[PDB]
Image (cartoon, grey):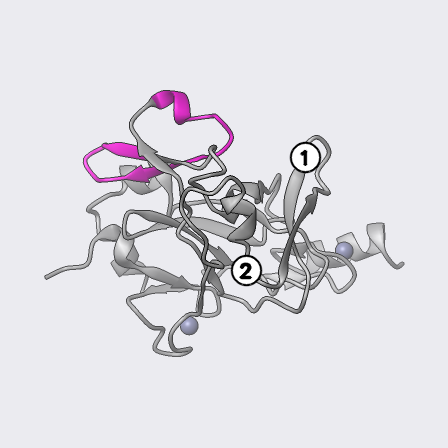
Amino acid sequence: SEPQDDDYLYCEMCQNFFIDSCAAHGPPTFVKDSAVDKGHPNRSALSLPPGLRIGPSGIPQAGLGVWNEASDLPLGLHFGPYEGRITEDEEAANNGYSWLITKGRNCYEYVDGKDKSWANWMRYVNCARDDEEQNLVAFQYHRQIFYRTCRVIRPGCELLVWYGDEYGQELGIKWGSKWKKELMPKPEIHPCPSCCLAFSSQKFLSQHVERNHSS
Ligand SMILES: [Zn+2]
Ligand SMILES: [Zn+2]
């Protein structure tokens, strides 16, 4: 047996892939949705875990977003699966609430969370606009979409998701290549102490602090 491309997790501290639990850091924590019927009118809002808040986004024109409220979300915390209807209808593609799920050999499906009655709270999470504000990574695991924290998320910071090589077309194009296996050049995360951003180096963090907070 051989794990499939979407059987791996990524440890945000090691910055590398693992199966089941990280040899250095142990098993990741998966947060459970508050349980509610797959069918109620407001299921999505009610599936929200304690500690998070749906409310007006900090991104102009975004509408609603999801905010961290109670306490720090540790680094490498997992949410999901993203819920919705599975479909091959390309109309889903850019409908604002759908993710691509790849099945190998350039085949794809979508999980569509547009309908609040069959989706979960993750439908309200807005996409990051840049690397500095992104604090969640959407990635495929067991043919399903999960979000992991790529930062310590402090109280009052908006949850903002984006994606990379563990998702969609990039994932689909490398499928079967064992590239995750071969990774097992470490990216750096340098968070700002005064706002919700983080930077890829100390230089960039200092320039930011000096333009935005203190010089
Ligand atoms: Zn680790
Ligand atoms: Zn800042």
Pointer 1 residue: 63
Describe the element under mark 2 as helix, strand or loop. loop
- Height in image: 206 above or below 13? above
Q: Nearer the viewer, residue 104 or 65?
A: 65
In reply to whether residue 92 is colored magenta, the answer given is yes
- The label on residue 190 is none
Where, quadrant-wise, is the N terminus in this rendering? bottom left
Amino acid identity at mark 2:
Pro
In this view, the residue in front, 197 or 71, is 71
Residue drawn 60% across the image and 56% down it:
200
Q: Where in the figure is residue 167, as x and y percent of width and height?
A: 38, 43
Q: Amino acid at mark 1?
A: Gly
Counting other residues with Cα less than 10 Å from the Cα at mark 2, is it few (<14), some (14-19), or many (20 or more)? some
From the Cβ of disc 1, is ligand 2 less than 8 Å away?
Answer: no
Return the x and y of residue 96 as percentages of the image width and height. 51, 30
Q: Which residues are magenta?
A: 90-109
For mark 2, what is the residue?
A: 49
Quadrant in the picture for residue 74: bottom right
Q: Is residue 73 left or right of residue 13?
A: right
Left or right of residue 156: residue 138: left
Q: CA distance from mark 2 to mark 1?
A: 20 Å
Which one is earlier in the sequence, the residue at label 2 or at label 1?
Answer: 2
